[PDB]
Amino acid sequence: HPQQINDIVHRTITPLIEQQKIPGMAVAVIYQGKPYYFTWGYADIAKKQPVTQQTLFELGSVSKTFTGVLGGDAIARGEIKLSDPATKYWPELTAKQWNGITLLHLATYTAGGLPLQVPDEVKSSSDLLRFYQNWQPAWAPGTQRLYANSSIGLFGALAVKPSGLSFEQAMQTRVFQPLKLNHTWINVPPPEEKNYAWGYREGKAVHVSPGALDAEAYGVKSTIEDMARWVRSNMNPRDINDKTLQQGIQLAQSRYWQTGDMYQGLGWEMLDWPVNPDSIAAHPVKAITPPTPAVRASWVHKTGATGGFGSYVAFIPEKELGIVMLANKNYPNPARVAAAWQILNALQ
Ligand SMILES: *P(=O)(O)OC[C@H]1O[C@@H](n2cnc3c(N)ncnc32)[C@H](O)[C@@H]1O
Image 1 (cartoon, rainbow, N blue to C red):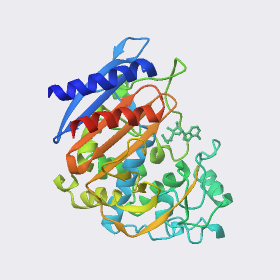
Image 2: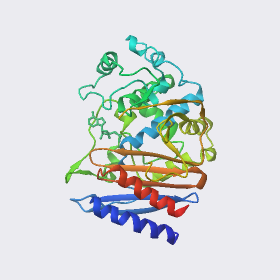
Image 3: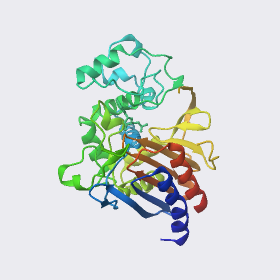
Image 4: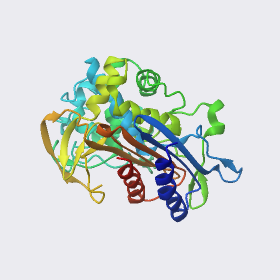
């Protein structure tokens, strides 16, 4: 490691762990293109199993970045357009409030107030259809952003329909495998279970429960090494020898809407670099026309949580600088962002 990386990471992450009382943590700092790894504490407190570079953490909503990119890849293939009505890919969704709602709206939380959570009793395909059929928008499409699992969750499920594959099969074959993310899972295979960290909520060991559209909205588990590779792939997509995937990664950093200081991509969210560290409910959106092609001078990021895990990813493509922070405790987002900003700001 470059000493300055060690110095700033030790300075920054050590206190964070102490005050947030985080039981285990992994961090990757991407600096001049290369990854540097750090680990702390335990994946399993009871068994005193240390966090390693092979420890799997629940990504929570960081999963949305994978879904956004997979959608981008489908657009690149000509399988979908974001301007297409959602009903084009689910004709059984006949209720009139769906007229005018597009894949873009689903992907970017702008469909008009889809709920943050899919109702907990929704399990089957018929349950899911009935849920969407009964949903009533609070706003017209394309006018308000309400960050929500039921929105991008449906986007992911519909985006993969033309492929003929399940969402998991599409993600595995079109995103995970081409990028050599060989320890990244929607469903952790039994032989890999020993590396799956427990999450901790009020001292209790927990893993995320099954829920409708979980794969699409929050269900990915990954290692610090794979997540470093993910960040690297999104920072320099032109380094990928897979045309539609490269194009998809670029489309996910297109700026489709603006809300205050931030811009909504597909899964990824973006702000202009340099950012004010203090700048990082529903809010009105303005369409950006044409959507701004991925801006390399951006803070590109996404936070994620499950009951037992807190995750954060941020990168600045212009500077070849990025960070992944994975912890097996859900701790406040401002703390994650503050630590990430301190580390990247020191290395620019
Ligand atoms: P992102 O990390 O913002 O959000 C995804 C996390 O939210 C929780 N989640 C989604 N859906 C539910 C339901 N129905 N009930 C309780 N919690 C839910 C999970 O923690 C996701 O990881």
